[PDB]
Image (cartoon, rainbow, N blue to C red; front, top):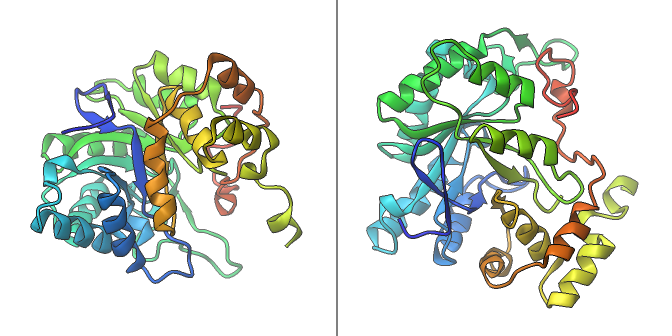
Length: 315
C-alpha cells in the first residue's frame, strides 16, 4: 500500500499514476504480459484493463509472476477492469466481472467501471453489427447496472466501483438515484492539454468524484501536427529538460487528476516515474490551461448514433 496516492470517496486509495493495458491492434495480446512485467519493474502499482481489451489473462499472468517471485504482493497492486457495452443488463454485470476474475486468476479487482454509458446487443461478440456494419444498440436502465455494480462491491468482487465516459448529466442520473448506496469513485475519460476537461473536472470534484485521465499524450491526418509536437509542451520540456510527454503528465497530476499512460517501449515506461521528480510553476500551469481546444481524439465514432452517446453535451 505504498503509493503516490489519492483517496476515493469509499475510503480506498488509488495510485495517481497507472499503466493502461489496451494494445495496438497489430500486437499479439501476449505483449501485455511483457509490458506489465516491465511496468512492474519500473515501480508502477496501478494497472488499467477492461474485459474488452482481451488482455486480462496476460496482465494477470504478468502480475502473478511478479508476486510469485516476490517483487510485489497482491495488495500492492491496484487492478482495474470494466464491464463492456454488451454486459450492462443488470444480470450480465457480475457474470462478466466473475469471468474477468477467472481470466486473471484473481479473487478481486480493486476497481470496476462501466466502460461506456451505452448498451449493445448481448453477448459474445464485442461489436454486434448488422448487414451494413452498424452496431446493434441495446436499451438498459443505467441506474440498474449501477445497482448491479453496487452488489459486486458488497460481494467483495471489486473493492471500488466507478464509471467511464459519462457526461455530467449521466453522472447526475447516478448520483440522484433513489436509494443510491455507493457513488462512483471516479469518471475515467479522455483528458489532455488540448481537452483539459475543466468543467467535468470541476463537477466531479464538487461531487467527491475523482477524474481519471486516458489519451493523456493525445496519412495526412496521421502526419499532421500531433499533440506532443505542441510548441508550448516542446519549450516547457526544454525549459525543464524533461520530455513533452512528461510535461503533459505532470500538468494532470498538479490538477489532482489520476493519470493512466502506456507505451510499447521500456525506456518510455520507465520515464513515467520522472513525473514525481519535478514540478510545473503556477504560471506554466496557467499557460498549459491555455492550450484547451476541445480536441477529442477518442470520440468512439461508431457509437455516435447511440442515444446515450456521451460526447454531444458540452461536458
